[PDB]
Image (spheres, coloured by chain):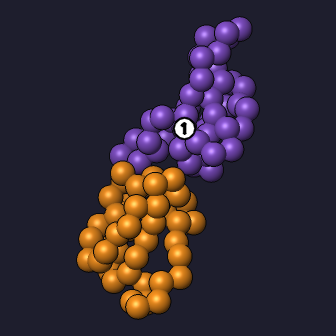
Chain colours: A orange, B purple
Amino acid sequence: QFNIDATLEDVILINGTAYNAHTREEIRSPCLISRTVHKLTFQYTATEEP
Amino acid sequence: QFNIDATLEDVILINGTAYNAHTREEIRSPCLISRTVHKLTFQYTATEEP
């Protein structure tokens, strides 16, 4: 759970699946996480290594 | 629930009580919220107007 602090600025999703702390919305790369997803949790994917 | 995005930079607690999204830790002014408290929710206090 990488805290989204003001210091990190921006984070990109190169090739993998990431989830939010609350919604845990499914995301498919390539795409920018965007500041909307406040918290960035994670899970161990199988098909594509994140 | 003011999302703590990189655009806002920093936010201060002048005189009031604020809570985090998950922990909802009790905070009494004056003090800085700090990036640790990631998502800032709120509640209607009575004794001291936030």
- Give left or right: position of B9 versus B42: left
* Image coords of residue B34 (percent x, y): 60, 44
Residue occupying the point 55% across, 34% down: B41
Residue occupying the point 57% across, 28% down: B42
What secondary structure is found at the residue carrying circle 1?
strand
Residue occupying the point 71% across, 8% down: B47
Looking at the rendering, in which quadrant would you find the N terminus of chain A? bottom right
The chain letter under disc 1 is: B
Q: What residue type is labelled 1?
A: Leu
- Give left or right: position of B35 versus A25: right
- Give left or right: position of A49 versus B35: left
* Image coords of residue A32 (percent x, y): 29, 67
- Displayed quadrant of residue B45: top right
* Image coords of residue B25 (percent x, y): 71, 38
Q: Which of A25 and A5 is in front in this view?
A: A25
> Label 1 belongs to which residue?
B40
Q: Is residue A22 above or below residue A44?
A: above
Tell me if mark 1 has few (under 14), some (14-19) or many (20+) residues whose alpha carbon lies within 10 angstroms of its own: some
Residue occupying the point 29% across, 77% down: A29
